[PDB]
Amino acid sequence: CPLMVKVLDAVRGSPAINVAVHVFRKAADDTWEPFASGKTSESGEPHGLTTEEEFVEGIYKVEIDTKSYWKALGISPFHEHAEVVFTANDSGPRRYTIAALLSPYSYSTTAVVTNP
Amino acid sequence: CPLMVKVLDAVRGSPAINVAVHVFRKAADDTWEPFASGKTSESGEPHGLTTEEEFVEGIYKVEIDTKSYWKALGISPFHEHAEVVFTANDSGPRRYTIAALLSPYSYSTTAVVTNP
Amino acid sequence: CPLMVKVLDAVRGSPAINVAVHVFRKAADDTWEPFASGKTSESGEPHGLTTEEEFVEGIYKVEIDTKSYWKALGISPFHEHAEVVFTANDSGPRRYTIAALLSPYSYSTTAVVTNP
Amino acid sequence: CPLMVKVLDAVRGSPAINVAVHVFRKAADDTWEPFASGKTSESGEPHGLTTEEEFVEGIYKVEIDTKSYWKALGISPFHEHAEVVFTANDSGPRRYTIAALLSPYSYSTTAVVTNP
Ligand SMILES: C[As](C)(=O)[O-]
Ligand SMILES: C[As](C)(=O)[O-]
Ligand SMILES: C[As](C)(=O)[O-]
Ligand SMILES: C[As](C)(=O)[O-]
Ligand SMILES: [Zn+2]
Ligand SMILES: [Zn+2]
Ligand SMILES: [Zn+2]
Ligand SMILES: [Zn+2]
Ligand SMILES: [Zn+2]
Ligand SMILES: [Zn+2]
Ligand SMILES: [Zn+2]
Ligand SMILES: [Zn+2]
Image (cartoon, rainbow over all chains, first blue to last red; front, top):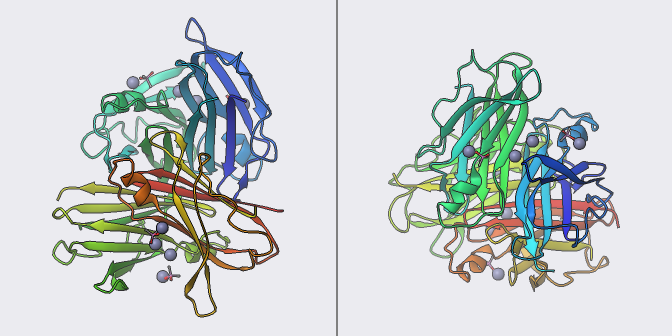
C-alpha cells in the first residue's frame, strides 16, 4: 500500500473505528476529482486505498470525516472535518502514511514518507 | 477580537512570523466567500481579523499558508497549507482562538472557545 | 514573567483551570529542588512563577498534574502527569512559554523562547 | 509485544532511527527500577521490550532520549528528553503503544491501549 491513513482517538486511547476517509486528486482544471474512499477498520485504517501504479504524481487531498465520527459517539466536536493536502510522487514512488490524532477540539496530522 | 489565529514554529520555538492567513465564510450556495485576510506579526497572529458584529453565525474556513512559510526559510515542507473548518456563533457570540503548531511534516491545530 | 505555562483542554476547547504546576531546578548534586508552584487560573496559566532575577541559568523541570485534572472531571486518564525538562538562560535571559495541550490519552507540549 | 514505542521525526517525516528508549518500573520504595531498554530501528521502534508475563501490573516510566537524537543530527533541541509515566495492566493484560512525535522545540505523545 503506497498510501496509508491511520486515525487515532485521543479521548479513548484507541484507533478511531468507522471513520470515513476520502482521497481526491487535483485535475487538469484544478477541481478535486474523487480518487479513493474508505472507512477505517478496527485498526484505524481504511482498506487498501490505491496501488503504486494508480498513485501517480500529482496533488492529493485526504479528508477525514472527524465531525461524524465524534457525533456518533455522542460528542459535539469543533471541526467539520480534517484535511491533508500534499504533492505526492514527484521524485519517483514513495509510500505515504498520513497519521491523524483526534480530540473533539483539536487534531494533529503527521506524514511519514518512505521509499518503497 | 472575536477571532484570533496564533501560529507557532516547532522547529525554532518561536511564533511563526509573516504567515498568510485567510478566512472564508460559506455562502448561501456553498461557495467559500472571502471573509478576511492577514499576515502574522512578530507575535504569530494576524492583525484584528473581524469584529463581533461582522462575525455572524455561519461556517468558516481558516487557511494558513504553511507551505510558503517553510519554503521562505529554505525548507521543503510536506503540506500545501493547513486549514480549519468550523461552525461559529450558532448559540450566540463566542471568542475563537485557532492555534496552529507547525513542523515541516506535521501540524496540530486546536480551538479555544470562550464567552465574550 | 520570564517563565509562563499555558495549559489547554482539547476535549472542552478551553483553558485547563485549576491544574497544579510545579517547577523544580536541578541542584549541585543532581536532585530536583523545588523552585516554584502554582495552579492555573481561568486563563490556563499559573500566577507569576518567578522573576528574571531568580530565574537563573540551570536545568529546570516543569510538572503538570494532568491526572488529577482529568480525574476531577470524572475522566480516567492515561498519564500520571506531564513533565517538561529543559536547560534555561544559558546564553543570557530568555522568556519561556511552555504550552501543554491535554487529552485523556495524549498530550503535546511546545516551547516558545523569546528575548526579553 | 505488549509494550511498543514508536518514535517519529516531524522535521524529516520519517521514523526516528537510533533513539534510546528506557523503561522503568516503580519499585516498592518508590524508586525507578530499570525495566527494559532499546534503541529504535529503521521503523522507529525498539526491539521487543518485554513479554506479557514480565509486564506485570505497576507504574511504568518510558524515557525517550530526544536530546541526543537531535544533537546527532546537528540540531540543538529544547527538551532534555521526553517521558511518559502511566499505570499499566491493573485490570488485566493490555497491549500498549506509546507514540512520540518529535520536533526540536515540541513533542506529542499518545497512548493506544488495546486488548491482547
Ligand atoms: C462531511 As465531508 C468531509 O464528506 O464533505
Ligand atoms: C496557497 As493558498 C492556501 O493561499 O490557496
Ligand atoms: C502527582 As505529582 C506530578 O505532584 O508527583
Ligand atoms: C539522557 As537520559 C533520558 O538517558 O537520563
Ligand atoms: Zn465524507
Ligand atoms: Zn475542508
Ligand atoms: Zn494564501
Ligand atoms: Zn485545503
Ligand atoms: Zn502536584
Ligand atoms: Zn515524571
Ligand atoms: Zn538514555
Ligand atoms: Zn524526566
